[PDB]
Amino acid sequence: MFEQRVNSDVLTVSTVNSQDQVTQKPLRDSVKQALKNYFAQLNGQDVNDLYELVLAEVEQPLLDMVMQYTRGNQTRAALMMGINRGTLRKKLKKYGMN
Amino acid sequence: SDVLTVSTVNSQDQVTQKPLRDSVKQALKNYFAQLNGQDVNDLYELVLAEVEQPLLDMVMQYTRGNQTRAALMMGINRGTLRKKLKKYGMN
DNA sequence: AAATTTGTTTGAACTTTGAGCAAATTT
DNA sequence: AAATTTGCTCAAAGTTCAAACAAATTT
Image (cartoon, rainbow over all chains, first blue to last red; front, top):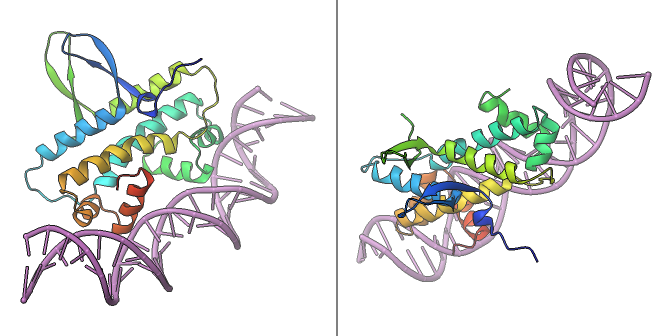
């Protein structure tokens, strides 16, 4: 057959391990790391917009990368992400990618 | 100046931060590399799923389970948070 | 000159929100 | 015993959507 590829390992980054060998951990794990790192560096300072902070840090490069792929075609890009053409264009405005 | 970041090692064994947005690119760069014009259909709800999950995973761990502190921390409604927790089944 | 995409608008379908309250749980 | 948090449900506020369709651009 084909071999399973869990959604965990659909999107993946390159890491180095204890034996200095290149392996591919999930993006999940990068996100986890970053948050662990963000809390530790926080020091009892108040936070109240973590969702939008993360979302910004993820939408931008998804958009960046997807528009490169469709050589700048929105209809394709929006179809490709699964979102209305108008909201893509709204998101794009928000980060100044138009 | 950039708050969301991850650690990296160079060949000369030095650790060093880089923004998470640089990871997300790589992932996508890689996702697209390994497709070969196979249609992609629902990519926004995919990455979102791969980012919501460990964000919820970590903020509950941080707020010791406190749904209320968690929502307030994330800047979303207390009900939205319940719904997202059903979505990935983290009851 | 043919097809396809942009840039808009419209209204309907859906989602998030703030508040309210009893009942359960933590302090 | 007091304070806070859960689990719910209403409504209003806000976003996403598909569909139009000229006007611009690309095949």
